[PDB]
Image (cartoon, rainbow over all chains, first blue to last red; front, side, top):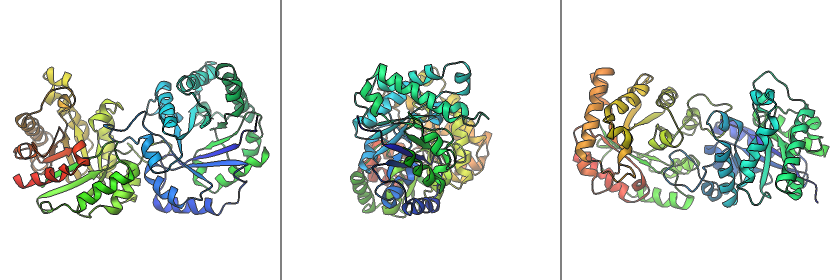
Length: 252
Length: 250
């Protein structure tokens, strides 16, 4: 029924010092962006800076962890449980990021279990999907994205607190450039998959955000697409340019 | 003489309320001198700032893991540089749970140890054999191979502690004896003497990472080649203080 609220997530990845975090947070705190009714803004620092960011960031921007454990805490040295994030009043978590799928070998099932467990503790989830250059060149884009999405869908009963991020991994460090039209094509096919395989209502209300290369310059052209509901920003999330990407929400 | 070393691995446990209680209990503790025992406490990443800001300054804070190299495009990982930036002096690397559950290879662990040392972190480097490996007669083959992957990459032995985890005796129904701990620690120290140097063998702490409680701490701690403990679950409880007090056995 109601329009999907534009969503901008900033994934800091494995970057930051206390000094850099203070500079980034000060820059965001002084930013003048569209209303909380027009855009939902989430910033995702490394685990060790979650307390500093949550304590100092403007209350109308929300904090995400970059990962959490698949289940209840216990004998999992080095892992952070969903209930720890809830305990520290961290409302969001990024799960299934292409870097964790590729470098740390997180399976679609492992990601699905994490999403279900995070939602069960009351966290909101940015659930990431995306195909490699090999998969795209093989003609497997929608087979891979549908399979990643299905592993999540099979474990999720309530999509209200889920945002899906499409990462064109094929266009990240390969020399290949994703067009806005190519982004819109995958977002459209993914939403049609949700409509047929979950429900018309879930398809209509679930934000699908673009996790490819976005800057101030291309944000309105990418953002001004029928099935693109915002961005999961990588490196630019550390820079003032992030504010220009948030401002792309006015295109809707 | 090697200074007795007691690490407390909280693992994936804690809330702000539980952390405050644990830290208050440690802050009120009366334990042996800084000459007799070195104490390290390892909370989850998200509680490192709270623990570092509130813990007695003569106990040291460790992260439970860090990334293998320089930060960048590694969503969810915490770099050695970040820990140094937050004045976290120690890191646990190659814990049996990360080797077994998260499939960290001996080479990956070795690279993490080298990178952590290079940023100025002190490292508790963990090694240990499974029940299958122990029953196959492969205990010292496995421990030597895991240690070699680390030793090949170490740039400062002063800042390394080795933790032997008898993984075969964690949730299997098997009980690791003081004699079995002593045997592995002695053979590991002899490996260091032959493969690194007599001086590194003589001065490097080898701590026992098996099931340690108030009751068995003095008998384990009294062994010639056991230089202390990496404590699991008991590290969350007042009993951790009784384990630190085992250092007086040396």
